[PDB]
Image (cartoon, coloured by chain):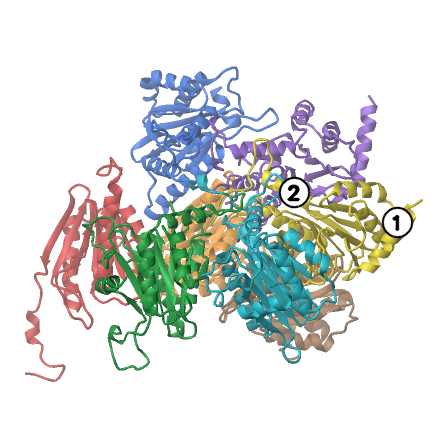
Chain colours: A yellow, B cyan, C purple, D brown, E red, F green, G blue, H orange
Amino acid sequence: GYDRALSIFSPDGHIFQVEYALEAVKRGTCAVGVKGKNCVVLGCERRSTLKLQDTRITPSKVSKIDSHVVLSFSGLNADSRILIEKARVEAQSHRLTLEDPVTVEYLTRYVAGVQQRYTQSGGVRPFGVSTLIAGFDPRDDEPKLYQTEPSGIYSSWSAQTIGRNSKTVREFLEKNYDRKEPPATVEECVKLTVRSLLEVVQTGAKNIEITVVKPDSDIVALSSEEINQYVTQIEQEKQE
Amino acid sequence: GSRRYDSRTTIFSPEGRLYQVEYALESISHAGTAIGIMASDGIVLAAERKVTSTLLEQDTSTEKLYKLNDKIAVAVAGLTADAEILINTARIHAQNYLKTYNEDIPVEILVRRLSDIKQGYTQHGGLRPFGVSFIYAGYDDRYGYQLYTSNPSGNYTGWKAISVGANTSAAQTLLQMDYKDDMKVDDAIELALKTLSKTTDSSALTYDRLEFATIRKGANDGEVYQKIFKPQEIKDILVKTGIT
Amino acid sequence: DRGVSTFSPEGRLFQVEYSLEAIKLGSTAIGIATKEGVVLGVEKRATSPLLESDSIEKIVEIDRHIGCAMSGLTADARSMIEHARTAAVTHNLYYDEDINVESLTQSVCDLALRFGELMSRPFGVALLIAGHDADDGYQLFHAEPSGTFYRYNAKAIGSGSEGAQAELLNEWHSSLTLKEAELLVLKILKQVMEEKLDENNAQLSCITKQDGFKIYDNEKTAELIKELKEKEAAE
Amino acid sequence: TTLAFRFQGGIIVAVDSRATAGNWVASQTVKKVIEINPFLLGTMAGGAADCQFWETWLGSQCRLHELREKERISVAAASKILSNLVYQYKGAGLSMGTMICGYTRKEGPTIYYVDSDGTRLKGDIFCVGSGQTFAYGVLDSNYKWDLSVEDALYLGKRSILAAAHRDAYSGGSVNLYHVTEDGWIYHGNHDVGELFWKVKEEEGSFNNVIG
Amino acid sequence: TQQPIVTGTSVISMKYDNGVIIAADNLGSYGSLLRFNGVERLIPVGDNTVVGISGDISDMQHIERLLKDLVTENAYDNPLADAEEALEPSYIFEYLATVMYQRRSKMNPLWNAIIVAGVQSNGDQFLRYVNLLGVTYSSPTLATGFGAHMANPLLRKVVDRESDIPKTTVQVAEEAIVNAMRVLYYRDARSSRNFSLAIIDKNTGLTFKKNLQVENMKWDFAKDIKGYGTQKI
Amino acid sequence: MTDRYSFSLTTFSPSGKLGQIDYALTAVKQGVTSLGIKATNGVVIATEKKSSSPLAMSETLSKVSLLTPDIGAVYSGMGPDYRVLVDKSRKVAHTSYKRIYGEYPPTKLLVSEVAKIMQEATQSGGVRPFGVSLLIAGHDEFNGFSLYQVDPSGSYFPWKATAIGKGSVAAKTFLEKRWNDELELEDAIHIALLTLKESVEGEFNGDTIELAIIGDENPDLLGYTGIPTDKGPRFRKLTSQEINDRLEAL
Amino acid sequence: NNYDGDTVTFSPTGRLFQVEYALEAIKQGSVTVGLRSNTHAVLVALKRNADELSSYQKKIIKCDEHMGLSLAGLAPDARVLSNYLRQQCNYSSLVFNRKLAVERAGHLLCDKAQKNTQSYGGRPYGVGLLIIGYDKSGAHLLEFQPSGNVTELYGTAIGARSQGAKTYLERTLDTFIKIDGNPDELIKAGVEAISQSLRDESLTVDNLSIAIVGKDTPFTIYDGEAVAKYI
Amino acid sequence: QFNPYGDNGGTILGIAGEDFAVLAGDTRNITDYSINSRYEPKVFDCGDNIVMSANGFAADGDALVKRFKNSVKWYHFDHNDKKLSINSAARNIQHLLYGKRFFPYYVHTIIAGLDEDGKGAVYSFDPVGSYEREQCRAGGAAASLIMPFLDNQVNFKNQYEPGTNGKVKKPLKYLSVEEVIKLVRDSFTSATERHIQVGDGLEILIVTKDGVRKEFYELKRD
């Protein structure tokens, strides 16, 4: 088999293939994760240079891993499918052996482990993908939001963004998100997520996707009209 | 040793692009234009043959349009030899699904698997990627009529109308201009040909330089027919729309 | 390019030397060994204030009698920890006893040089392995990606290592109490850390014969930080 | 003879200590309860080696789960690790009758029967071994959910004693355990030789033996 | 798993004060006691060790080649191959013992009983037995097959215990072995009159007697025996 | 030791060219001219026998090869690469078709299998593409007569008539003028000999020209009688004498 | 220059540079001495520390009851080769009930090192070993180099400034060779030998490491207070 | 069909005192009704004050002892010459035996030594590695003859205090090494009389903190 070490160390102690993988993520469409008091919301950018798209059938940016956990991403779309498949298989494998669905932390740790393995295996390049993994542990009402990246490091976030112009929307969240008092309701949390994307997106038409995850496997994707009402409300309040 | 002669086909550029994928897409951009248009009551596939010779056997020739099963066809843009490898794989995957579930494979499932094979060649194995872009035209009982494209990266997306190969920039602007959602198949046929007629690098668009196919519900009561147009049938539809 | 297992003209392995550079970029980790126990402390170093710091696990349990602190590409440590835990539990299964801290360290270091053209590159992470056994008592080891390990009375690894190690040289004596060692780790961490040290951006742990390996709560570490400041102001 | 039953006060686990090779009594001081962890117990019936080796290995697998998840393994998960292992070896000739008993906050007191054919069962009462029928006769007759801890302990002890007497391949001594929210508690080793005569005198039972 | 076709019968051996003696008849026995003469079953390995093999002849010839192969291998890059680093009986036995046990554990045994007779470098007598099961044991007298049943009882009269070995001379031991070989000829249907005898002596080295024959047999009394009880003529 | 070359030797250049395929086609261009013409009642394939030495026996080297009783192949480019492709082509006609369906494959499907082998040499580890273009002439019951070209890329196209190698550009122009849809087999052979005379410089006779046809069934070449359905091979290689007869009335 | 990329490439003068670079790792390594009489063979090693808070890197590894080595260079490679020697010593015992000859130990290390100098992808060993043993032909001292060259010697030294100790042993040859049935005096000669390779630093209690094997002496390592006698 | 197992007879006996332990075995090796050897030891010093015997099929017994002796050697190499405690040795032997669960060693294994508190220890194993610490254990051919005697004379089973109406048991106590060797010698002379596979010689290995001592005693040779 093809054995070549593609991810190796440089004199300055960097692994360029892992760092070039992060550049692929920076090129990816923006993805944001905001967790409230009793919910987590995943916002995702869709570039508007593609008209005549069939939004019915086009792969959605937010993927259910199980009935209670969701995965969004920024970077190479083709690469994301391999992580989502492996994660979905591990979710059903965990239920089969432990007789309990995965914790959000466990599913994160697994995906991060796969991403890490591809940074020191022969013949393979790292995943050009960072993920936001959100949901609720079984029989638990505490919201969970984790981030992974090509190197294989993962960590928990009150709120976080990845992809193109993520530094701009991270700036917004860092001053607009209060640790002591997070978004109390679903409406408040969705609004703050939409607001944070409106700093970067362009137009609030068919460019913003919102997915609301609640305790006990309660995940619903918002339609155009539903999201459009939040865009209309924010722009009228802005003009002051 | 052998390390000296390795092109390393599966590595990132400092900008975080896949060299071989980008160069494969450059290859495909020189290939004959393929257009897919999805209507409310069917799908059109239209493709331009690469600079035809007068002594080429036109009637018993297959370059662009291939049948995957009774409900799904693809238009090819790139290396024909590479496409045939992937097509035979897709034809087998479709029959494996039918054998397992006793149901025709949903369009997206076939597309995802073929796209996942392409992805593999970009992440491991040290081989060159497949120099091929596909337009998938299909029908299933879940989403009805569907258009998809895949490219050497292994990324795939859904479309109401799309072009691959040469002059896609020009072709996509013309489709975006004249396409509407309540469109009929007969209208979509006219759009596909008019688009090729304006984007073509040839002096004039003729029957002998075209491959054409429709997926309609034209057969009796809730069943899908795949019509791969004969030379004489292309000649007729080209006169009827008033291009010749 | 060039081979992965290539020697330099000086007689060092290029890829091992380059990995040591990755470990210098890593967040600081300090270990101090005493006759009352071994203390392990780390700089958490959150990249952003929105990141929940309690989710940064750079101090890890291997068995009840062996702890572990890491510095460098911390993702690389996951499989090293997995192997160490498996080695510790497997040895207990085969011999019905606790495994020696040195033997556990030697097991982890046997992975280090299992790379070439096995895994594609050396590990980009250094480990401080702290533990107790009946034979050699309270021990602190430094496991490098070179496959070499040294025993230490005290040791610092990461960005602030060369500064911290010079401070440990003067401060460490053979009669240190556990309470004294805790304050000393916190003192030297606050010196070499960029941001100001508190209970959220720094973490303490210890391993004692009696209670085994324990990661300190933020409430407990907060009191030791408050105790440290008062004692430095007192003279 | 091994039994485990659920009641108001938690789980009672009682086992004999006899090991036989044909009609030869090999030992009377065998530990048929593996202690796994402070809230987990395993009973052993069938092949002595199969049970001892695969339940000592189950304790190792349970320890690894707690190191990787920073949480004690559930009785359900621990039982399934053992049942999935024996199923791999199915048809190779492993012989095992085992009960995994423990308390966790999320499950409460739980008993799982696991055997070498791959059967995994959750239940309130189980009796496993050659003397299971003798144990069942006593347990089922006097079993109440609202039994006192003192009465439940005695019933388990009494049920093993009944089996030790009538079954040729059960005997030696009785080992008693009690499992609650605070963990499992050892209630000592009772030699059947001394126990039988005490029980006969105090209870007024065992009238079939030359008093 | 196999079945032996052509086999060799008993190998007999004993220790004396200054060495060991080993003997074996030269016959190959077939299926229903069919005979075949011309089979040497004494393998001299070096000049301090003789290996006596019984059981399947084909497996014996394989072991013979292994021992020839072993001597060649020991000489490789060995300046002291004919001195301090020469093959010892204990080395040769342990090799054979290892092979026999790993062959039985693979369920493809070498269908043989082997006795390794020799003198060690320090002059200690070496006598040990290994068989197709990899079972090993040592004794002042060792014999295989019929020899175990008939030769051992005769040899144990000369050397019943370890303390008898210093009192036993080579003249006495050789007589005992030669007498035992005649008894086996009388009573074993798979034995032959022709046999080979090897003496390994620390002082005189290894003596190898070949083409030996059973002599001073008693048959004269057969003329007096008539019928199976009541017959007088 | 071992084959450490498990990586592609053919890769995309920044311009999107596959260098090794382009260079393989250059090797084909240097190759001796071969051509194929399809008639209504048969197909003709022809090539020059460029003899390395006059001491060499040009009969022993066969540029026109039988693949099945009803399919023949000629090439332009590297002879050795052709010889091993003929071997692989004959075998794959059996392993992947005849041993399954109990009949010889149709022209288009055997061509498809040859194309596949050549595509693999374009993408597999540690190999260069095949330095040949094949013209494959064949007959099958349901498709009738057909002529296919196969390129180093693995691409194949059906032709009414074509030429490959040294003088292909000039040869193709000549065929365009002469070819019609009403050509009989004898007419196509005549045109083939006219077309090939242009590209040949030295001696032009039955000993320097190699020519085969896919035409009527040949009972005399079957080697047995008694099975009415077996009527014999459609592939026939013309003799030195049979070519010289058609060069007199030229 | 162009011919040092891997171990599978000869230079135009017929040199293997990757092997010569591996040899360089040994010169950087801390000094170790080996010497023998007819009755005993001794290893003396100067152990190296990272700093005053660190332990001293162990240089001497036991292989069997009658054989062991000292290392100079990559310690992990010494662990790989010493583990291989342990297995070969162990194979000889289990299969042939035979203590492995020190000469055969040399031949096996040579052949293992050689394969790593002729194959692409692999690298040469980056350590030098001094093997001492007592077998059926008496006391033995071997010098291993990762080129594969093994050499039987009365005495030698490897590591930084080893030339000093090697010169001393060359002069002392006639004296220390006849130290028969006197372990302490043969060690003293080994400690006086390694002393010729010291600069600024002197031999301390936790710095010096001694090992000995002989006629009625199993391979035993002396460290800490046990080597205080010889300072 | 080839049968890979055989019975080499013999019988072994382990007894644990307060500050000592003994492992005894007869020196007779047999096959069917023949004597192979009158002196073939099967009780071995394994180092680290552990004595071992694997009685039954001699080939499997030799193989297991060889593998355990090797396990002790590699424990020293891998764990800085650490002493292998008797409890650790016992767990190791379980894994050696269970390793061949589906092609077992046909031996009954007994090891003896001192525990980590310096008190006499005996461990006994089945062929597939189930093990238990015991004060007293006999193994092999004549186990059934020796074991009930040891129950009576070592553990004082079925003995009551004279006059107490069989209410007060005879109190348990540690026996001296001298008293234990008497019970061993009488156990084996008794077994020699009534078991054809037992006789020729008795070899006792005694384990104290001072090390491993041997005693040999003749048995009847019939």
Q: Position of residue B90 (x, y in %)?
A: 54, 64
- Tell me the element at label 2: helix
Q: Position of residue D77 (x, y in %)?
A: 66, 61
Graded by Cα atoms within 10 Å as few (under 14), some (14 to 19) or many (20 or more), the crowding at tag 2 reads many
User: Residue at position x 48%, y 49% from top?
Assistant: H178
Residue type highlighted by circle 1: Glu
Quadrant of the rendering where the N terminus of chain G is positioned: top left
Looking at the image, is mark 2 or mark 1 earlier in the sequence? 2
Q: Position of residue E176 (x, y in %)?
A: 16, 56
Q: Which residue is mark 2?
A: A22
Q: Are marks 2 and 1 on the same chain?
A: yes
Mark yes or no: residue D42 visible: no
Q: Nearer the viewer, residue G117 or F226?
A: F226
In the picture, residue G135 is in which quadrant? top left
What's the chain of the residue with tag 2? Answer: A
Task: State left or right for residue C152 relative to residue F42.
Answer: right
| Numbered label attached to residue A235 | 1
**C192 to H16, vertically: above or below:** above
Graded by Cα atoms within 10 Å as few (under 14), some (14 to 19) or many (20 or more), the crowding at tag 1 reads few
Mark yes or no: residue H178 visible: yes
